[PDB]
Amino acid sequence: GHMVTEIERKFLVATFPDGELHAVPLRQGYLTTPTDSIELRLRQQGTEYFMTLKSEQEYEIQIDVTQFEMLWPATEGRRVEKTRYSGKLPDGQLFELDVFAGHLSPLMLVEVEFLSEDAAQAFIPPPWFGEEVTEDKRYKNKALALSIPG
Amino acid sequence: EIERKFLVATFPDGELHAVPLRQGYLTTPTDSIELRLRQQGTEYFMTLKSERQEYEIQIDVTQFEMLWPATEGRRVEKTRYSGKLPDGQLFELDVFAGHLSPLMLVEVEFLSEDAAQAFIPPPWFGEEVTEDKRYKNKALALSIPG
Ligand code: NA
Ligand code: NA
Ligand code: NA
Ligand code: NA
Ligand code: NA
Ligand code: NA
Ligand code: NA
Ligand code: NA
Image (tube, rainbow over all chains, first blue to last red; front, side, top):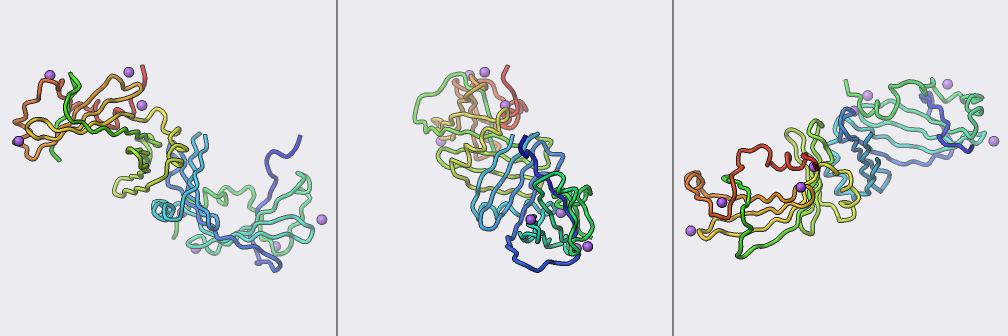
């Protein structure tokens, strides 16, 4: 049957790449902590703003900038801010490259999407990619948000 | 803030101003924060509390009704009537809707502890529940049908 869940691998970045990149600044943060009965997340994607509620079912409301900045401070300590660059490798695989801000600096991650779950296994990373972290729990989004400075 | 609250034995006559109210909790009391939605007549709010910081944003009706379903089981819906007793004390009288029917509560505000302690309820008031934890707002919200 057709693709249900995307197939991807994620790496550190040894060298920021050259080439055509499209930049989007991103700020996202959790109002809740993982033991809460629900997950409530705020995100800014460019110039649009959302609050998401999940219970384990998913609600998303678009909010304006003033609603977002009034509530943002209640995400302190559980946030990820980064600029995301979208690009394409020479063979055509699309990538997203995150350059993290605040205490997660100097982290940079690159995530690659594959059309076949065997092109994924055949992938040869280009030299600018660092070590693979696909399986490392610490580099998942929520782990990154919940980590702490110092 | 100086107040006593009672059941209501008889709905009163006289000048009453009615406000429909709907208010519900997205969170459960063990959560790290409390997030409440409320509709107060024609304006709508989401409140976030964490014991302290408090945040309130005004939302529109569409945001409110999109999120309202995630308050199910933790809501109070009621019509609130504002009036004044013959001696001038202001009262708020709540007529509860859904499963909290047929509950009705009346709360009175006083300018002194002495006036509060001297208060003689009028005959339309029922038994006092100022101290009953069961009749507190969040307790009412968290109680369930049946
Ligand atoms: Na954090
Ligand atoms: Na190709
Ligand atoms: Na750092
Ligand atoms: Na490399
Ligand atoms: Na309830
Ligand atoms: Na008087
Ligand atoms: Na009932
Ligand atoms: Na009575």
